[PDB]
Image 1 (cartoon, rainbow over the protein chains, first blue to last red):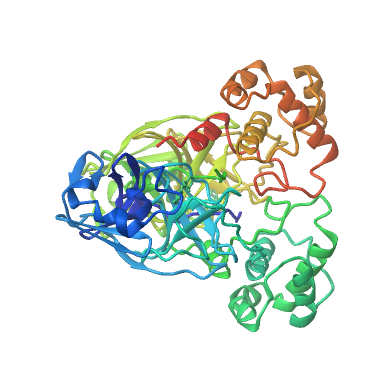
Image 2 (cartoon, each protein chain N blue to C red; image 1 turned 135 degrees about the vertical axis):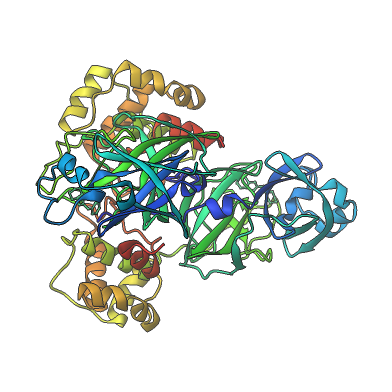
Length: 304
Length: 304
Ligand SMILES: O=C(CC1CCCCC1)Nc1cccnc1
Ligand SMILES: O=C(CC1CCCCC1)Nc1cccnc1
């Protein structure tokens, strides 16, 4: 019993973290097989960061200008190329710690573990959601860039996120491992407002199922609702509209708990309309939206 | 910027996790040098678990009855002994992944990372506090026992916690790595009520400093207070009394932010007396007490 914002075990990712230095700027790289993936803003200087001409900047850089250090051993860089907003540095050595891995572009609402890194060294790990507005609410300083998000299916590490920039609002933006930004963000030093952030309704419901499973049930009411009723309430409170897809994905939690999805929606509806009246659910005084139905099933059954 | 309930990178601990099986019961072991540390209730059967005579039970067990498996290779067990509530299984092979480590008994209020494990396999990692009543609010199922808590100072893993039992209230109890329970708990199948849990006041203050640093400051007021005034308010609300020690430890956050500790106490006082009025601090609708002043400094500066 008990329920925690649990991150994936970070060991398989630790073994892939390197330091990347170009001119003066240092940040993190991801060493998989004989390629190191890092943010392309590694090649920038403070005078460039306004509106960097990454193509013109990269012309001026040679394999020898990319200092790649794994612990206390340097990697020889035999190739460099720019794919969208990441650099691929071909090195002469395969990372002997390369886990089974894929590159996956996650969907907003989907969760992942971040291993925050500085100078290619891990500092810690936490679980995150891709916000509906394609931002993450991270813990990232100068030198945390190139830290990656991931999921792990048994032995396969799915890399979904590379950290690039912090918005003036203090929220985080980043790319997939093909260096495509999640959201409209560009790697520049300009004000870039994040759209309206909605609450990930299906994740709140999944978390309400986790609560019931772990014995927090005071919020179960004698009401039901309809997708269309519930969604009128969702709109008001900037929740994502609930679809039959979302309901289908909650089926395992519905089946286990025997609480129909639309009944739980009616619990959610009442919590939105009346607040929590100074009570808590799984040690939280607000509605947690960063556990997927998958996350709840995994943790509540103990998948490894 | 941003602030997260961050766990230590779990890789150094993953490499120490094994499976321990005695009779039918399976749970987790910790393989360091040529010793495997596991909960002694591994030797119990469901008929024993009421009031187990661990000494008499252990008589009946031989080195060959302790099946110790690291991934898909068995360890030969050349010795077994009981220290308090853990078993030390001497194996013929040193764990080649043994990190630098110590065994440290933590103080209540101190935090640590848990790597929850099943069948010697990691499932995930989260940050925890030893509650003032020597319980932890974990995420642990059947087979999670022998999962360990830890801190990491650069390269040294300090093991502080081994998970043993869940109380009927669904809160967790466990030992240091010398198998001494934190708190009054015994490894039996009896109702064992946990004392009153207080809020770890110094950690809330440290978290209030983290909030101010990350730009959440709406709770800063024009008031101050005194240790003795503040502590009258602490009592009412079951906060731990604040001491000069606690104030001394907040000095780095006070100095950085230039907000005297007793001023922040006066912020805390008002939050206790008036609640949060439906606002949030670092994405929380209640007062977080599971970040130490050390934790806040580490994360806000980015120690690795
Ligand atoms: O965002 C920047 C600088 C950006 C990076 C992209 C190019 C313009 C400059 N640094 C940073 C700081 C804290 C957390 N994350 C990232
Ligand atoms: O607590 C028990 C059984 C206790 C263990 C000690 C001896 C009496 C039996 N199992 C469990 C379940 C979930 C999380 N943690 C532990």
